[PDB]
Image (cartoon, rainbow, N blue to C red):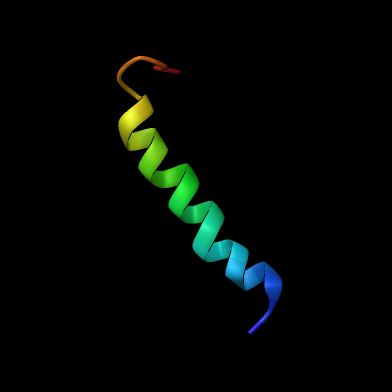
Length: 28
């Protein structure tokens, strides 16, 4: 794979879950 596609595992599991959590006290 590529380090970037490893960051797809990282960054997408950062952005998406956090929006789902942080939408509550950090709504934007």
